[PDB]
Image (cartoon, helix red, strand yellow):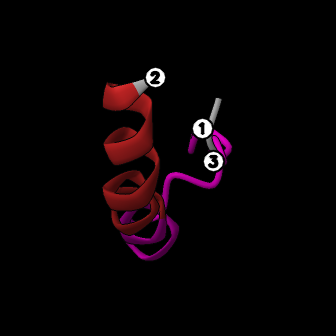
Amino acid sequence: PPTKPTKPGDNATPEKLAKYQADLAKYQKDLADY
């Protein structure tokens, strides 16, 4: 599998959440292929 990011639970601030979302752009891309 590709680089899977950590889930924003307690750190689910709009800041880190955006980082997560931006990283999903990379993750979910390879993940969809996988």
Upstream in sequence: badge 2 or badge 3: 3
Answer whether labels 2 and 3 touch (C-beta < 8 Å). Answer: no
Q: Is residue 15 left or right of residue 29?
A: right
Residue 25 is inside the magenta segment: no
Q: Which mark is residue 34?
A: 2
Element on which disc 2 rests: loop
Examine the image and state in which quarter residue 7 appears: top right
Q: Where is residue 18 drawn, in percent x and y?
A: 36, 69
Label 2 neighbour load within 10 Å: few <14, some 14-19, many 20+: few
Cα–Cα gap, marks 1 and 3: 6 Å
Upstream in sequence: badge 2 or badge 1: 1
* Label tally: 3
Answer whether labels 1 and 3 touch (C-beta < 8 Å). Answer: yes
- For image coordinates 46% across by 62% down, the residue present is 23
Examine the image and state in which quarter residue 1 appears: top right
- For image coordinates 31% across by 28% down, the residue present is 32
What's the residue type where badge 2 is placed? Answer: Tyr
What's the residue type where badge 3 is placed? Answer: Pro
Residue at the front extreme, as displayed: 33
- For image coordinates 62% across by 41% down, the residue present is 2
Answer whether labels 2 and 1 touch (C-beta < 8 Å). Answer: no
- The residue that mark 3 highlights is 5
| Residues in magenta, as a range | 3-19
